[PDB]
Image (cartoon, rainbow over all chains, first blue to last red; front, side, top):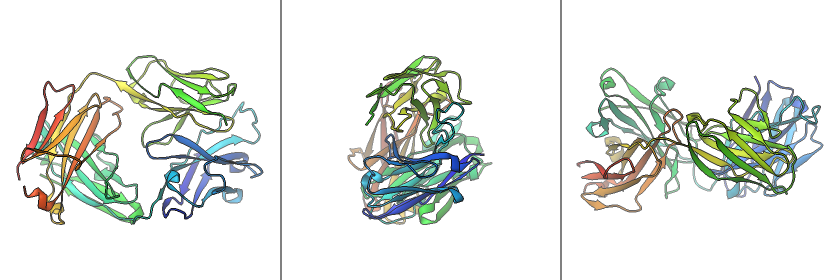
Amino acid sequence: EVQLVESGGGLVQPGRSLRLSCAASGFTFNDYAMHWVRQAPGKGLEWVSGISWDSSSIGYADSVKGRFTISRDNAKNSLYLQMNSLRAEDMALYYCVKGRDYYDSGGYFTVAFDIWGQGTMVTVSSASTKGPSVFPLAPSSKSTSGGTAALGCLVKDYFPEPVTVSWNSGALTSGVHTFPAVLQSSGLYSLSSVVTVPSSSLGTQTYICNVNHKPSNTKVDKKVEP
Amino acid sequence: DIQMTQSPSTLSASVGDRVTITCRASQSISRWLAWYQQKPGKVPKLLIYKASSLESGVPSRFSGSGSGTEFTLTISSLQPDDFATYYCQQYNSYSFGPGTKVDIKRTVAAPSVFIFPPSDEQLKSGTASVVCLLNNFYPREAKVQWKVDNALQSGNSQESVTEQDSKDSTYSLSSTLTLSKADYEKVYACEVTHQGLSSPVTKSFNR
């Protein structure tokens, strides 16, 4: 299976550096141009940089020229982006992306930009890494309607993104709404994750939320009840 | 450089409608155009390359056309799961268009309104969060006010909204009232307005 696994994203002061990496597998890495593409929160896709199979040609968007350096190590099937003098505009999700085959000039049997890495987050900020507090949203008379109750978890005061939330270790997906994070004036993120379930199941089932905030090495399970 | 533009920037349309999204290049790029679908929280997915070639295993309701300067992506019969932002891209120097965000039109559906007071656990550390939940409504537009002992609030609440549900095309919405433990020792009410409710609705609790 054809894959691009990214790493090296994280939190860095304005003016400082980070190196992204991307490990390729399931295809002949040596034969392909490779690219970086980014997406700032709630905005569009922006092509950032590309590099030929043998590194003999390299391209940059005007907004990164002189600050970013793309490179590759074909012996290690790896693509890198060295980012220096990081600023606000560079805060984004960064995608590793598979380009054109060297041999197929016209793309008569090959298509470019078909395989994307999962993304890695770059946060540019002087603020501190902080784990979330995880509070229950308890089901009650005031969170019920006919045959359904709503319950949840409040995941408050973390920096930077992201945080993930599951219910009962993935065994409960149906009826889950995990809300997008919002920035609180204080400069920290917060979100809720809720789920609606049969009201009669409150007696038979246990509902636990699994919160993971990798940047702070915080894992928390919270059981939530009437 | 080559500038890519798209129109309209957003559109809403019913299940079964024919939708047409337009992409434009500042200068001629022949058939060197690609189209991407991005669902929120997921990586972009290539739908069309070389203006009209369908990428493998992409449903046949998607089609592309154009050569030169003007391009279209057509969804012949829109489905609930086609909710996304669609980006064109010039296939020579890799630059993207700004995207068209497609929403699914469906029948009006009034929200279910639930309220949650602060947890005991939280209260302990001197902060209180009241959460009001609007569940499974359409359309996305809504109004939530906070009242405390009848006093209407300002600036001390933040809202968040989910993406369209891919089965039933509804939205849900959280409003979170933030107050100190101090201030919270002082009947808390979430009031909601929406096209589906004949008149506004208020969920509240005491203490």
